[PDB]
Image (cartoon, coloured by chain):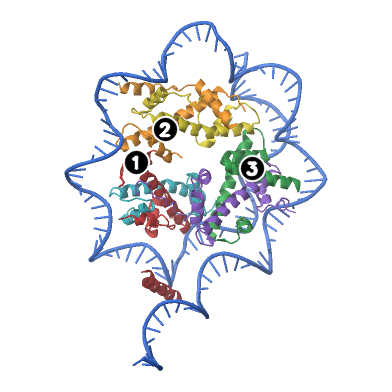
Chain colours: A purple, B cyan, C orange, D red, E green, F yellow, G blue
DNA sequence: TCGAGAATCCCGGTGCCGAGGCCGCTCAATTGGTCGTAGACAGCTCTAGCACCGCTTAAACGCACGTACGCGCTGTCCCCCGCGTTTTAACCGCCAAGGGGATTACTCCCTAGTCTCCAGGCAC
């Protein structure tokens, strides 16, 4: 019985606890810690995959491309607060012609 | 010369990606100079990474670590 | 008398903005965000210094933005595009 | 040489089928791929690495990531200088416009 | 043979929206993003642990780190998901 | 009422300290607005720090660590 | 005018390379008895912020000369730009050498743990 099947988790909570142990970060890791790490990573993954599913829905393509992920990460102010500095490979840029040139 | 390999219509298409109506003839040399400066500023760290590692291949892991060190992190090539 | 105050406040390397109204302002924002919290005066003068540095950086960024648009008096749009290169 | 025959067939298919500046702005804003020619950029980064080198090798994906990051930084600086250009009542940009954004960022 | 989240990303994709396909480069971008936010929350949790005399990383350290990094709606939904999963874990051993 | 804790000649003297001579009337209100939006994140991060410290008084080391996390490191108040 | 025959629009068949699934598997995930060690609470003090105001006190609020210049209009003037035309090297395919990356590990060498003796270090 793994620690993931004790809470319905899918992200590898035992592996994550192992990388926190043998990963030059801290000394002790509580039992309530890596299930919560698995929880917040699962929430972030569910948010970005739902945004990618919407981006695949409204763009009539049944697959996930990096342009869809770039339009996911750049058209949300919470995602511009979180990851407004990093970029996506082959993601392109935001199509926004300014009003003064129009 | 290899600094003029990125020619005038290349920077024109880059500006049309960035949304410019009309551009001037003084832009291209300063664009190439700031591109050489940014390339030097990332390549110095990216080659000190591969010079410490007893290697001669500038690996993609080394350039994404050097990009993460200098703020502008990429996704997909490690990390 | 234009160059008088520029050579006076810059050479005097002390603070210029208030302390106890800033303590009232930080009490107001902790009433907005938190429950009253006691505040060390070193933390209040550290917030004062950080606000002073952020403001002088914003004004020294808009200084050349004023002369860029053939102006001298800074505008409200100058505190709308200097934030674009500040995050 | 079946790969050569397939390449000639694809080249023939591209030659037969695939073969007021306001359109290019909205055209190149929805493009996703790279826009810098590959092997002159590789020769340029080979010349840049010759200043800080020894026969240092190069993986191809590293030069691809470098081209992507440099294109991203250039379009970021260009998108930031367009606002300062139109702020100074200039539709046409100038080298003075790419001096303040090169100054106030650091 | 590297410990990759790829099968787990496909698994959590197949629960809410199974109609969308996933490529290779986009999946590697997702894996690098989740590893980046994982190491960011790891170094922030280790930093907050080494701040105020608590070497054991409990749920308190990482909930303070989640409240620290994320914006308000994101930290609210993240602390909701984390409290839900920690009750489901501490209840079912 | 503490939203007007700062005054207009104070912003004028701060502009003379920096180099801004001619000031518009909207600049002081926009400075109050950007001060409002600037202090709020660091102060609520210090509230999160004090909640991590489970006390009432905000200590100075929490302020230094909050300004270090925000990217506005201050020298002289810790270490 | 009938009809047979050639051309084309639209409908049906088929490569094809990327997404999806799968058998074999093999160093990690689980649980466990224990065990030195973090850590949470509490008397108790001590110490830093808060209010009132004694006593002054520069400084902001706001209105009045006045002229510098932001915005808009008018004329100027020229420099990138669309377009045509000529050149040119990028991409692709392919032949070829070979060179560092990757994987295995052993003596040796440098470190965790151990106790023992001494010279730093802010307080009086």
Please name the residue shown 56% across and 48% down the image.
Answer: E36
Dot in front, 1 or 2: 1
Disc 1 and disc 2 in contact, CB within 8 angstroms: no
**Mark 1 → mark 3, Cα distance in angstroms:** 43 Å
Residue F38 lies, with reference to residue B2, above or below; the image says above
- Does dot 1 land on a helix, a strand or a loop? helix
**Mark 1 → mark 2, Cα distance in angstroms:** 20 Å
Please name the residue shown 54% across and 62% down the image.
Answer: A62
Q: Which residue is mark 2?
A: C57
- Does dot 2 land on a helix, a strand or a loop? helix
Percent x, y of residue G30? 74, 52
Please name the residue shown 60% across and 38% down the image.
Answer: E47
Q: Is residue A38 left or right of residue B53?
A: right
Disc 1 and disc 3 in contact, CB within 8 angstroms: no
Q: Are marks 3 and 2 on the same chain?
A: no
Residue G42 lies, with reference to residue D86, above or below; the image says above
Residue E7, quarter of the rendered image: bottom right
The mark found on residue E79 in the picture is 3
The mark found on residue E36 in the picture is none
The mark found on residue D87 in the picture is 1
Q: Which one is nearer the viewer's eye here, C69 or D61?
A: C69
Percent x, y of residue F43? 55, 31
Residue F77 is at least partly visible in this image? no
Q: Chain of mark 1?
A: D
Percent x, y of residue B10? 34, 56
């Amino acid at each position: 019985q793994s620690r993931s099947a004790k809470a319905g988790l899918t992200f590898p909570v035992g592996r994550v606890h192992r990388l926190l142990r043998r990963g030059n970060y801290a000394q002790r890791i509580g039992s309530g810690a890596p299930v919560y790490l698995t929880a917040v990573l699962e929430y972030l993954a569910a948010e970005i995959l739902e945004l990618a599913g919407n981006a695949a829905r409204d763009n009539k393509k049944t697959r996930i491309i990096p342009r869809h992920l770039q339009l996911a990460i750049r058209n949300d102010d919470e995602l511009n607060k979180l990851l407004g500095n990093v970029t996506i490979a082959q993601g392109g840029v935001l199509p926004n012609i300014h009003q003064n040139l129009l | 010369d290899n600094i003029q390999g990125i020619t005038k219509p290349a920077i024109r298409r880059l500006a049309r990606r960035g949304g410019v109506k009309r551009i001037s003839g003084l832009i291209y040399e300063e664009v190439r100079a700031v591109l050489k400066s940014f390339l030097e500023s990332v390549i110095r760290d990216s080659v000190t990474y591969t010079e410490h590692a007893k290697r001669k291949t500038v690996t993609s892991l080394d350039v994404v670590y050097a990009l993460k060190r200098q703020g502008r992190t990429l996704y997909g090539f490690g990390g | 008398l234009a160059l008088y105050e520029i050579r006076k406040y810059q050479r005097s390397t002390d603070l210029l903005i208030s302390k106890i109204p800033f303590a009232r302002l930080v009490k107001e924002v902790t009433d907005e965000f938190t429950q009253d919290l006691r505040w060390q005066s070193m933390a209040i003068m550290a917030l004062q210094e950080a606000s002073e540095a952020y403001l002088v950086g914003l004004l020294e960024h808009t200084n050349l933005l004023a002369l860029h648009a053939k102006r001298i008096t800074i505008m409200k749009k100058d505190m709308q595009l200097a934030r674009r290169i500040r995050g | 040489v079946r790969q050569k025959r397939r390449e000639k067939q694809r080249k023939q298919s591209l030659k037969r089928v695939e073969k007021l500046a306001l359109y290019e702005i909205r055209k190149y804003q929805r493009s996703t791929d790279l826009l810098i020619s590959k092997i002159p950029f590789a020769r340029l980064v080979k010349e840049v690495t010759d200043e800080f080198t020894q026969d240092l090798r190069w993986q191809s994906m590293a030069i691809m990531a470098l081209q992507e990051a440099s294109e991203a930084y250039l379009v970021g600086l260009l998108e930031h200088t367009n606002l300062l250009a139109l702020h100074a009542k200039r539709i046409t940009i100038m080298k003075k416009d790419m001096q303040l954004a090169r100054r106030i960022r650091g | 043979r590297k410990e990759t989240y790829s099968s787990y990303i496909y698994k959590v994709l197949k629960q809410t929206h199974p109609d969308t396909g996933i490529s290779q480069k986009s999946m590697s971008i997702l894996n690098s993003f989740v590893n980046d936010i994982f190491e960011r929350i790891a170094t922030e949790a280790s930093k907050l642990a080494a701040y105020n005399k608590k070497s054991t990383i409990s749920a308190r350290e990482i909930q303070t780190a989640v409240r620290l990094i994320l914006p308000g709606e994101l930290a609210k939904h993240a602390v909701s998901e984390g409290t839900r999963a920690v009750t489901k874990y501490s209840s079912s051993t």
